[PDB]
Image (tube, rainbow over all chains, first blue to last red; front, side):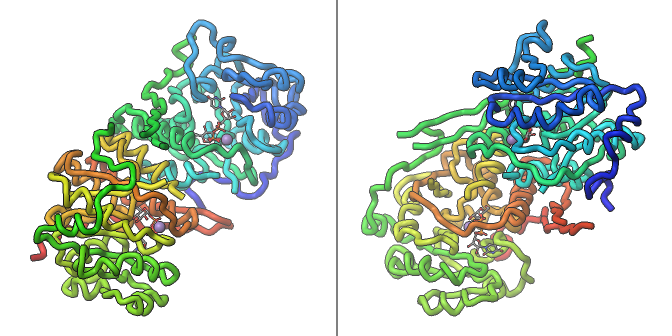
Length: 282
Length: 282
Ligand SMILES: O=c1ccn([C@@H]2O[C@H](COP(=O)(O)OP(=O)(O)O[C@H]3O[C@H](CO)[C@@H](O)[C@H](O)[C@H]3O)[C@@H](O)[C@H]2O)c(=O)[nH]1
Ligand SMILES: O=c1ccn([C@@H]2O[C@H](COP(=O)(O)OP(=O)(O)O[C@H]3O[C@H](CO)[C@@H](O)[C@H](O)[C@H]3O)[C@@H](O)[C@H]2O)c(=O)[nH]1
Ligand SMILES: [Mn+2]
Ligand SMILES: [Mn+2]
């Protein structure tokens, strides 16, 4: 009933059916992590039993953690890849977008799956539920999750999409950190910086491929780190810079400033520079 | 230290000085009200002692309340004006913007002051603190308040202004419902619909007059009705439609849709139609 292929109830496929449907295609899972020692182990544990089966490869993309994220991830049996190790020839920029872009060179799966590592008790069927439409359907090359926080999504992204890309008004969680896509697509797209990356991939895929190439799946309920408003303001600023750039609208490039007392002025970084398609780095 | 004339500490002027400084100029106060029976009395009480003094006129602009807002406001000694009564020749549209636009025909003050009527225990010095820069300074024609909720402001408006009108990045509460301005300015500007009006007046004033004509004043702490996220999403959508329109960016005109389960789809209204300057209705 939506213009977007949408699985509403717990998808029917089993691990075995999906594993059969792979048909030579490989699957890589990437957990980007910046200081998530408190949750990373449960997130890895919820996925590592699929390894050597449905999943051929699982990595943690360590985006410069200074806490005990790496040693706990290792202790959970996960391969940990720094931004440096993933693509040593290129100096590292900050932001999640960078990490996701770099994870493309540290993985070799025909299908790449992303899962945020700050999720509190993720369901072990997240990955299957996410690769469902890619494996069985035809035409699908991007799968976003949806779920029943949510402030930047409900106040910035979905209303802006309503404003500038109404065709995507039916995407329920455009910023979801849990999503999957073909390597062919991901290596063809540029990667927006910082927190601009999701909204960047959505608009670019659609612009390049239309809604038929996009699916979304219900994963139930999502719980994650509740961040302070100033950080969300910064994130919201970058989401806006990337969305505006994809719509052909010039963004000033000026970072958001916040005040909190004569007074204490702080400016957050914002970037208008995308990383190119990983294809060009062959 | 900001490019915007900013009074940070409780402004020094007294009621008497300000009353002296009027010099023939009149002051109208407008409280727009849509179903605020629980708070309207305290808001009127905090202002009515200035009437026949500093304030020459106080009205409640009733924007179609079906609760006991009108009878309580009357019982507090306030003149209550319906949208119909304010400008009977023109059929009524919904939204706050409409109410504020209409209040221009029901008032006759050289200076018009706006105060939201959902404020919990407002300080009786709000109006003086707001008319301070208009009465004493020269050049000022718009005064916004600022204060230590705030989600649409911190995630949508200030970051968008950072994106498209960085000169206003130093405006602390662009959506504040408490603000004052000259009749000359207000009757010269168009009024954006619904919740687009504040952000519409800010961008238009600045575009027409630059920062020097704009001031902002600290009123301390603001407390008001906490609204559910779907309503804030709708509000945020209209703020975006108006901001995009003022920046020369085409808005789709498609209202934001929300889902909440096979499912229950609702679309909120959005309007791309401004009311013209009240001047043209002479
Ligand atoms: O520089 C960074 C920043 C974040 N992350 C990781 O990215 C994930 C998401 O970051 P988070 O701070 O939890 O973002 P959210 O506020 O939850 O943002 C939501 O909305 C964002 C905008 O699209 C998405 O990027 C997020 O994935 C999504 O969870 C977390 O695992 C982080 O550890 C990094 O690896 N590197
Ligand atoms: O159709 C309407 C809607 C609202 N109001 C009144 O306007 C005021 C503000 O509305 P509110 O629902 O409290 O808005 P907020 O979510 O608090 O929005 C904040 O941000 C908005 C966007 O600029 C401003 O319009 C508001 O004044 C400001 O308080 C309240 O007194 C309402 O009674 C009306 O008179 N008519
Ligand atoms: Mn998170
Ligand atoms: Mn309010």
